[PDB]
Structures are given as C-alpha cells and as structure tokens.
Image (cartoon, coloured by chain):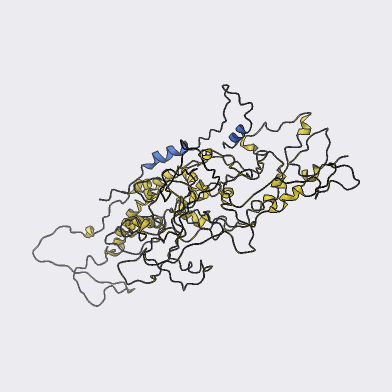
Chain colours: A blue, B yellow
Amino acid sequence: QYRGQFDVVRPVVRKLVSEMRQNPIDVLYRPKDGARPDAADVLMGMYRTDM
Amino acid sequence: ESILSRFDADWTASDEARREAKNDLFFSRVSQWDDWLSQYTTLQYRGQFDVVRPVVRKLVSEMRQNPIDVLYRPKDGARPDAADVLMGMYRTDMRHNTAKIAVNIAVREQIEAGVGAWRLVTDYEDQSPTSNNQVIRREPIHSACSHVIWDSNSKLMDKSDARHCTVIHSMSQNGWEDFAEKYDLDADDIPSFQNPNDWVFPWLTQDTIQIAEFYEVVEKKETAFIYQDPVTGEPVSYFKRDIKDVIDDLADSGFIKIAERQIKRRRVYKSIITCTAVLKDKQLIAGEHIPIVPVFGEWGFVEDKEVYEGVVRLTKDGQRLRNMIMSFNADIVARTPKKKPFFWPEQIAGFEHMYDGNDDYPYYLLNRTDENSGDLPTQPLAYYENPEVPQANAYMLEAATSAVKEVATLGVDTEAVNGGQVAFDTVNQLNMRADLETYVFQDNLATAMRRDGEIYQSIVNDIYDVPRNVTITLEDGSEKDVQLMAEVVDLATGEKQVLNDIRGRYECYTDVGPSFQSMKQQNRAEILELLGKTPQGTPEYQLLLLQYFTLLDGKGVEMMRDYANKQLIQMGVKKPETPEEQQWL
C-alpha cells in the first residue's frame, strides 16, 4: 500500500489543452451564387439574430 | 406511495456519502491546516501548516477581473428614442459595490472546493413596492462542505424552467429568523437526516432540530398542439404529443375549437416524500421562477452522483515526509546523551559534588587501576553520535518544490493576449451575462410605464365624430411644435401580463466575444494595434468631427447634446436617434 498519491503526470496534459484554448474564428458566410436572396428581406434579418 | 419517491436515492447517508462528503471536506482542509485521517500512532505539536495557499491564490487574482460585457445596443428599425429613459434598472445597475466582489466568499464554489451557494430572496420586495431600481447581486453564504447530494440528471447546463434540488440551510442558527417573514411556528420543524457526529454521544455543541425546505414538485409544461375528435371515446384523455407529422388539423372536418386545453394536476397529495405529516404547500412568490444559481453541473463522471477532482495534491505528497523528519531530528534533542563530561570517571557514585558548578580550579577525579588483565591504547573516541550526511533528500525536496514550478508553468504571462486563458475561465464564466434574460421571468403588474395602450388610451383613436373636412397641421401663429401635442394622434397597440417569451417588445442579445469593452471603446482600442487608424485629409476634416466624443454622455462634457441643434445641410452630419427637435429657419 501507499503508492496512490504520487500524481505528477499532469504537466503533459494541462499544458496541451491550455495552449490550444482560444479558437474563435469569427467569419460570416461568403455568399453563394446558387440562389438570389434579393427579395428575401426579413429573412436575412433573422440571420442577424443568428448570433 | 408518496412516502418515498425521490427518497429511493435519499436513504443513503452512512452508505454513499461516507467517502464523498469526507473527501470534499478533505480537499478544502488540505488546502490549509493539517490532515489527521489515515495516520496510525501519531504524535502532536503540529498542524498550523497552511502550505498551499499562495499558489492557489494566483488563480483567483488572475481571473478576478475579466468582465466581458457590453451595454447600450438598442434594436429596432423604427423610432429608437423609446429606449432612452424607459427602464432605469440597467442604467442604475450598480449601486452594488461592497458585495459586488463578495464572490470572494464564493471562491469556495470552484477551486478551493465545489458547490456554489447563491440563493435570492422573495422576488417582489419590501421597500416601496413597485418595479424598478432593485440592487441585489452576488451574495454567498457560510460553507459548501456537507451541502447537497442527489441523483437526477447532472448534464443540462442551465437549470431549464425551475430546477435545483430543495433549498437547505443546515448547521445554521442564523436561519431560524432568516424566514422570520414567516408567521411564527415556535421554531420546530425537524426532519431527520444529516448527522455530522454519530456513534459517540459525549459531544460538546449540537442539537437534534433540523431544517430543510421544499417548494413545488417538478412542474413540467406540455403543449402538444392537439385537436380532439370523438373516435375512441375513452375517458382520462391521456394524450401527450410533441412532433407534428400526420395529425395536423381537424378544423373544417368537424367542430371548430380555437381554445386552450390545459391539464394541470390539481393538488396531488404527495408532500415532500413525507409519511405522517404535512407543513408546507401552496405558495406564491410574486410570480415564481429561478434566478437562483447554486451548485452548477461539473466535469468528469462515474456513477449517478456529483463528484470532481482537484489539483495541488502533487505537492504535499512530500509533506508527509516533512512531518516524518520532524520525528527523527526531534529525537536528537531528547534521546541523544548530549555531550558527555563524565566519560572517563568510571567510579559510579563518588563524593557529594565533584562538578556542582563551582568556580574553583581543582576538580580531582583521577584514579584507575586493574589486576591481571592486559590492555592497549584504549580511547574514549567512540562515544555515540555518527549521523550520516542528511542531504539525501536534496534534489527530492527540490523535486517537490519544482512540482510547484510545473504548475507555475500555467498560461505563461508576457503581455496583452496570449496569456493564461484556461478552463477555469470557462468554469466561472458559465453564469455568462445572464442579467437581461433573468430580470423578467414573469410579468404581473406595477410596471406598465407604457404598455397595452395603458389599457385606457386605446380608444383615444375614435374619440370625436365631427362631420366635416379632415385637415392636417398648418400655421396658426406663434407657438407650435413644443411637445405635448395632440392633433391626429392614435394608437394601434396592446399588451398583457406574463407571456414569458414575446418579441416585438424585443430588447437585447449577447455581444462580442473577447475582452473588448463597450464604452464605444472601438474608437480608442488603438494600442492593441498601434498606427495607421487615424489619418486626415482635406475633406476628411468635416468627417473628423462626428465619430468621436467622450463616453456615456457625462455632463462634465456636453457637446452634441446642445451642439446637434441645427447645423446646416452643407455638412450633413446631423442625425442622432433624433427624438424631437426639428426647427425651421
């Protein structure tokens, strides 16, 4: 008994997950040419609230 | 069968929590002081240690301020000025400062331990009852240790409509009068649970009376979008529907309903898993919902239960060896014979005192003789002490300290971004700017600044029947456009109470990601990236005026309040939200 407490494996784990933390990638929808949302109107307004 | 219910999982105290509650205690009581749990044959005169406090204290100070919030973003395509003064709560948000930071006492909720305890009071409150200007935020309580154990869900982040457990205030004689808004029951309630002491009765300070409190049983809302044709004709309708696929609508195939079918079970006699007694039931707190935000869900799972794990235990795995060496080197101060003067005198008991501490020179103390033995240069040189070079732990104790170095590698700090962003940021940020979705969980009465056409004004539409021509405004002489004006005025509007999710009254949403502050800080954000943002030019001089002014209309600097009055069409810089003033030459 008493081998349980030694721990210390963490430096590998806690480092990695730390430096990959922020991946915000804020970009919006480079428009498609397939349809023509010219008359869409309030439709695209809903996608302002896609936030 | 109302004796048990949830109690199927609640009888376990001496079974389940024996290890769990004791380890939750054990983590926060390892964070300071001493341990005395797993030891055998232990000796005293220790226990003040408090070794780990600072290295944990870095975290709360790093994350103590990262507000991440935005204000004043009105939403509409119509005339905006209706938003200026019409709700004073959020312009008045902070009269709360002293206890704004009181989440210090709530630091028990996350790192030092789990289990945040935050519970608000009765919604609609005492002083001058009416709705606006109520300052309550972030008020923690005593201790998180023996707090809460239940088996339900432990997944959903938000508590949805109304769920946390049942409020409990335990080991608190301050709670007796906490509800003193009660009507007075003699201060005896006493369910029987939760025994901190147990087997051995010779105890100092405790009492038998206990308190735990409950409100409603699991109110779930159903809608189901059902039309009911008389086909099978079974009673007890027993219909629960969600997805619309086949059924659709029966309207012109028969009767037309256009009504509301509510099934609300009326007064089921199950009371708080109680057998022989009834006390609490049928209460209204304003309208009732949950601003309450204690005991959030967590990370890591095994069984149906709420459990986590900690961090700094990697350090004081070596302190047991400190308390170890305190045994070995304390044995020299006592056990060791301590520097023998008397070795060479071998004669046991001599005369009265040869060394009493006298200052006189002669001590005598020489005789030796032996008969038929034989000998050689016998020397005292042996004595006892030969401890060996106790540097053995050197790089091992530097390994225990460097184990604190390894956690000191967290989120290396240099400048600006690329800092210590960590999971604990997400762990305390889960509350996540919940004010403007919290404030209205119900609507009843006593707000009505303008709504529903005031419930009277709505007929101002049709008032006068005068037969002849309808004429718009004209030039009548001196006084004209000063406000409080009535000529053609009308109203189409309407409103009522509650309707918890409603838009067209639409207000607010969450804004913009990172540490970015909204004072209009987009103007001066600047040093984040240095040069190139503020050029000039011959025409741009005019354009240089409009985008920049100091923030939140502090009267220390006025400008565009009285500086927007007129101008001229040469520039064309005018329009703010433009509530009223339009003035001809």
Q: Quadrant of residue B168?
A: bottom left
Q: Is residue B531 left or right of residue B391?
A: right
Q: Nearer the viewer, residue B34 or B562?
A: B562
Measuring 91% from the left and 46% from the top, which residue is drawn there? Answer: B477
Q: Residue furthest left?
A: B372
Which of B565 and B192 lies nearest the eye of the viewer?
Answer: B192
Number of numbered labels in the structure image = 0
In the image, residue B265 above or below residue B183: above
**Image quadrant where one finds the N terminus of chain B:** bottom left
Residue at the limit of the structure toward the bottom, as seen here:
B352
Looking at the picture, how far across and down is residue B553, in whole percent? Answer: 72, 47
State the residue in front, B235 or B518: B235
Residue B394 higher or lower than B323, as above or below = above
Specify the farthest residue to the right: B477
Q: Residue sitting at 30 percent across and 51 percent down?
A: B389
Q: Is residue B420 left or right of residue B563?
A: left
**Percent of width and height locating residue B169:** 45, 63
Q: Determine whether B392 is above or below B193 in the image.
A: above
Q: Is residue B117 left or right of residue B392?
A: right
Task: Return the x and y of residue B159 as percentages of the image width and height.
Answer: 47, 49
From the viewer's side, name the closer residue of A23 and B578.
B578
Can I make out residue B556 in this image?
no
Give the quadrant of residue B198. Answer: bottom left
Residue B280 in sight from this viewpoint: yes
Horizontal and vertical percent for residue B354? 26, 74
The C terminus of chain B lies in quadrant: top right
